[PDB]
Structures are given as C-alpha cells and as structure tokens.
Length: 13
Image (cartoon, rainbow, N blue to C red; front, side):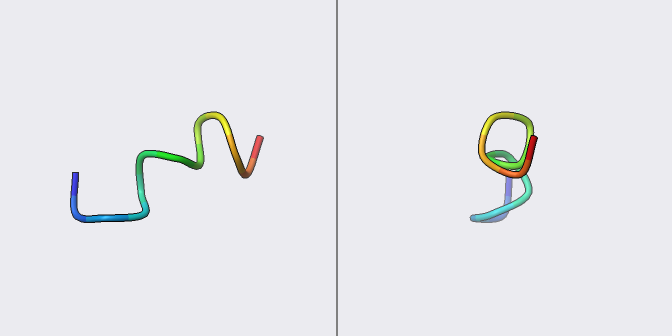
C-alpha cells in the first residue's frame, strides 16, 4: 500500500 489506495476499500466505499 502506497498511502491512500488502501482506505478506499473502507473510506471511498
């Protein structure tokens, strides 16, 4: 994980 494309799963979703 870089530093953002991980939270999507929870955040963005």
